[PDB]
Length: 47
Length: 52
Image (cartoon, rainbow over all chains, first blue to last red; front, side):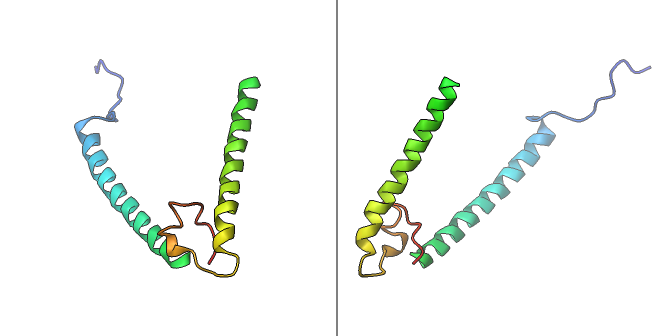
């Protein structure tokens, strides 16, 4: 019989989670940069 | 309660200064003219929250 509680979900900093962390962060920064660019664009249009 | 009350008062004071600075720096630009340097000098100087 198995001698381990059947817990399979990995933990952050793992290779599998690190890669999604890497990809997720890059997209978030890209989205954040777009947000900042749009905010500045709408900004300079108002005042 | 004392620490929380002090924390709020400083926040309220800080918010109070920010609005006052907005009034002092926004009134001169907006007396006769509508002209506020479209966020080039609206950010560095004071609150650019003027509608314009």
